[PDB]
Length: 48
Image 1 (cartoon, helix red, strand yellow):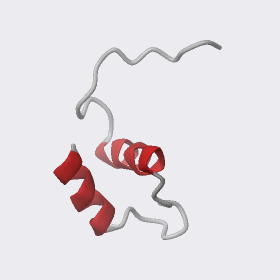
Image 2 (tube, rainbow, N blue to C red):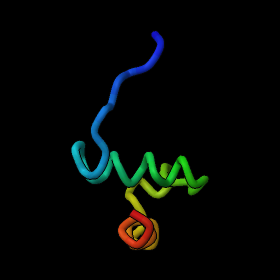
Image 3 (cartoon, rainbow, N blue to C red):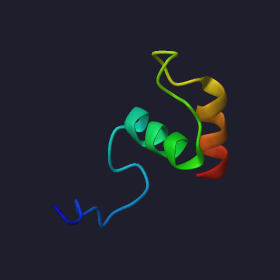
């Protein structure tokens, strides 16, 4: 129950999942749109 691992960063997992987690870590509400907003995706690839 303590730690799920994840030694690797970058896009090791699904892009959508990665962007959603990034969104959540930054406080972007990606859930209600049922899709990831391109704006968040752009910001994602710009920050990360």
